[PDB]
Amino acid sequence: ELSAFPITRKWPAKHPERLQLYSLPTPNGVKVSIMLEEIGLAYEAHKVSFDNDDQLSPEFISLSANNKIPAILDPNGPGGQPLPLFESGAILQYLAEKSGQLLSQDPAQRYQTLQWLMFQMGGIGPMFGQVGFFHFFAGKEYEDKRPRDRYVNESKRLLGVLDRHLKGRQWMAEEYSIADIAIFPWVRNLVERYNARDLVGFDQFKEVQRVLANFLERPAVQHGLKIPGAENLYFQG
Amino acid sequence: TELSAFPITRKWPAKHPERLQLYSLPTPNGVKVSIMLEEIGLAYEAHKVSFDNDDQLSPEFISLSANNKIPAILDPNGPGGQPLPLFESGAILQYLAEKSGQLLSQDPAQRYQTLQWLMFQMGGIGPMFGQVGFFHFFAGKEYEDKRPRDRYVNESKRLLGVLDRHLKGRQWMAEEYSIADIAIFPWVRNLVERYNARDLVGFDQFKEVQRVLANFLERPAVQHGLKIPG
Ligand SMILES: N[C@@H](CCC(=O)N[C@@H](CSSC[C@H](NC(=O)CC[C@H](N)C(=O)O)C(=O)NCC(=O)O)C(=O)NCC(=O)O)C(=O)O
Ligand SMILES: N[C@@H](CCC(=O)N[C@@H](CSSC[C@H](NC(=O)CC[C@H](N)C(=O)O)C(=O)NCC(=O)O)C(=O)NCC(=O)O)C(=O)O
Image (cartoon, rainbow over all chains, first blue to last red):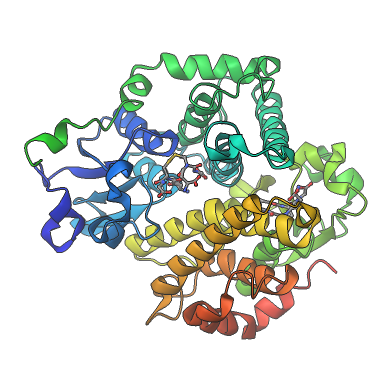
């Protein structure tokens, strides 16, 4: 019964028995594609193009109320009923709990993982994103650099928190988890796409560098970083 | 493990070591947790972490709360009866809901909708309303270039619209009062009261947000939690 969800009018399901992903390769979108690749859950990816204002369409918003990617529609949700969901961090937790992977069953570790996920969702994403605005997008042209410097300094502070935490450790929690999947695409985005490597003094965070490199070596990460592409759009036009 | 193993307790000793320890300040994020504790009826001992004194930047505080922020907790009666340290208001809300079996629906689909709205709060409402505070109420108000202010004001208006349209015909964010309401409404109150941003964000227009906020503020646990720690 996916036809009850208007999003499917705009991105029809070729495989309605599979989880539907509505996304774009961005630091938030790739959290979810990476997660799906890691856990081996079948899914059907759909490209939501910002160039066409797709994320502002009534069909998209009918599921993803905040007009943002990523969003999912899982036909095999609780009770075998479809589950609509947005917010990358909520989707990560949902998928971890659904699959039993990448979120510890040990309660204390569960909560430590959720803590670091929330740190990402409130700190890393929002603050690194402002560095992008003030160094890579329109804000880069603003002559008054006090705003830029606010967000750069805060991003450096957050990197320091990560760096100190990761000393002596492989991952944020005792096992690789959704907290890593949430954080490291954003670290990558800051130092690659936003061209902010020197601005945030990245070379001083040796532990973050080490763990980022380990993250990027993972085959599921390399796949998930690239998904969705456009091929799922072509037959429809 | 015993509570003295956590260096935070050197600076804020536990007078009641059998009780959950809260390290907080009356702020939109701190009151999420004090409100939650009041709602669920769990005993706790609150400690004031003074921003005026840079307490949140002390080594003792940071030893538990690694991001140097309030709120944080240390629950002696954590899972398996072992002490559990935790920071991030949204994580603490999930923890307390799961510990108490309150304020998350038994319907897992409703639980996930609730967690969605909690993440919307944690990534959108808190960070963006907080920037309106900086650029309207605190020192960023002095900046002659208003493009940053307007960026955050416009985004805050957009977020309020999302809430407002969602709340039409509803009492709460999910079908029952939940941790998502507790996360969101203290921030709405902060924006319009503390930051004096009521005209700035055109708050008058969000009739559903106003209605639900008013209901929220009538709850006794909310009134009590707003003032803790004193
Ligand atoms: N909390 C949400 C954030 C989702 C999100 O930001 N999605 C972006 C693409 S990810 S790309 C990263 C994203 N940037 C943007 O969205 C750029 C556009 C924005 N309106 C602006 O002016 O900065 C960002 O900084 N995010 C901060 C964070 O993660 O907390 C989107 O759909 N934008 C469409 C739109 O805005 O119309 C989540 O985790 O899912
Ligand atoms: N994600 C964390 C956020 C916690 C948080 O922001 N705590 C504040 C007090 S709540 S008061 C609201 C808070 N403001 C501030 O923290 C003001 C100081 C800041 N450094 C600045 O320059 O703006 C804010 O805007 N928060 C955004 C959000 O909730 O996402 C704190 O301890 N600050 C100490 C410090 O910065 O040294 C959570 O949910 O627990």
